Image 1: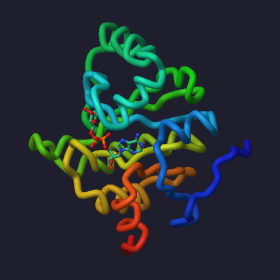
Image 2: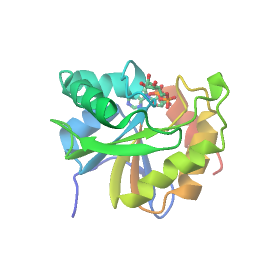
Image 3: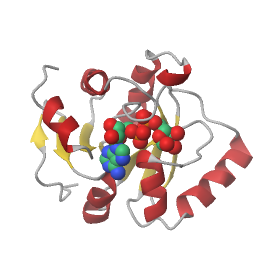
Image 4: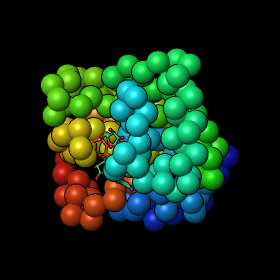
Length: 168
Ligand SMILES: Nc1ncnc2c1ncn2[C@@H]1O[C@H](COP(=O)(O)OP(=O)(O)OC[C@H]2O[C@H](O)[C@H](O)[C@@H]2O)[C@@H](O)[C@H]1O
């Protein structure tokens, strides 16, 4: 399919990037898959997760609570596919390592591997916020791991400007 993603800078054959709020991109484009930067409990408190969930009027959290009650916590580096509610067809919840709490940064590669199960994704930079991974490292792992088409939404202008003039 062809989506209405617009204004993205090309990084590689398959990776694109834009200084944008992932919630606003999802609202506008209504992609097949939006990625959430989750924790293992799917407790969507802040950052991407909290913003996505708020935009679903808490439906994402209600669904997530049932998912956890049935299946238990995700693995660090793991994922699950749930509804995208009013934002997207699906939300791929992906858990990057919480480097600030001692989790192995190498699991960020495992996290991004989940993206390869989907042809097209709108996504954030996993682990680059409250989880404490260096943002340029997360971008490099994404580029070096994801082979499917990924549209990265970077909320923070200063960060975007730095990332797009860094080597990959
Ligand atoms: N609306 C947004 N749109 C795009 N990028 C955003 C947005 N908000 C933040 N970012 C950027 O997205 C990147 C990721 O920041 P984070 O969302 O913290 O994800 P993590 O993987 O580090 O932490 C996961 C925890 O965050 C939640 O609390 C979860 O519930 C988890 O507990 C950073 O570069 C942000 O600037």
